[PDB]
Picture (cartoon, protein in one colour):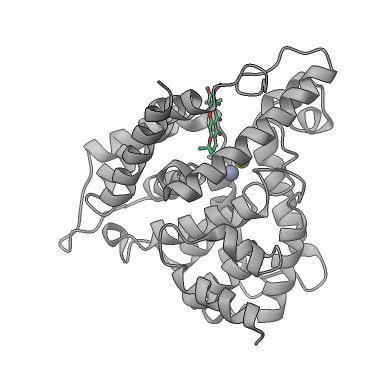
Length: 327
Ligand SMILES: COc1c(O)cc2oc3cc4c(c(O)c3c(=O)c2c1CC=C(C)C)C=CC(C)(C)O4
Ligand SMILES: [Mg+2]
Ligand SMILES: [Zn+2]
């Protein structure tokens, strides 16, 4: 190992921890954060042995999947996907969910997190509809990005030596496929309110086992937990250490701004958050936390109480900090 590989290996020791230095791992890995975090996680969960995944097929698929995130998109890139994968991996290990999910369900959630934004062009669903894009025409204006992320992520499995599921039974693949689709479609923000409503209902009627672990009889409850889990991981930036959070805010703002520039050059009304001439980055973060991120994470906290109390406290501190900069 070179000196660089020893440092990367040292950083990969935090893969079970909230607030892994995902940006450092991106650098140290040669802009391969998604490949090496996914590989590290499959080895940590013993997923190659369980599902008989050839290590070379895994790496080949991951590189190809990573290749299909856009290096020139400021936020929705391979780093974001590595971060959602890693955050989902931590959420799966929460005490209140020990022994709840099967290895197939855990693999579906981690796989869904990896592909969940692949080939993202850096512009919103609404932009794609408003501009009469091929994607919007293909998908009839409904979860346009999220359907595409799924189609690409599954299609790459067909490339040469890329089918990491080749040793699953036909039943296993079928169930995994449906779960992944269910999970990635749940990342569309236009599903957020109804997804949170179901999660609140579940919290209020929560049933536990004799060990104190969540009890989920049926597909409907199990998939809804997984959907919200990946959704929380997708919206986990404000819950991270401040120096991670602020970098995610810089990147999402740059990407929103470049969408607003494209709306400018096309004579369109500039979407909220996308006008770099009338922006309010701090106030918008506080609003997003207050109307979206905190309602979601407070409810997830309730579901697994008290496993997530520190994540929720970091969220609240980060909100107070952004708030404190406004006046
Ligand atoms: C117009 O609706 C908004 C809005 O007012 C603010 C928004 O702010 C966001 C801030 C974000 C991120 C966001 O996705 C948003 C928003 O989407 C956002 C939106 C759009 C909201 C909806 C369509 C429900 C992602 C990562 C971090 C770094 C946490 O920053
Ligand atoms: Mg997305
Ligand atoms: Zn995402």
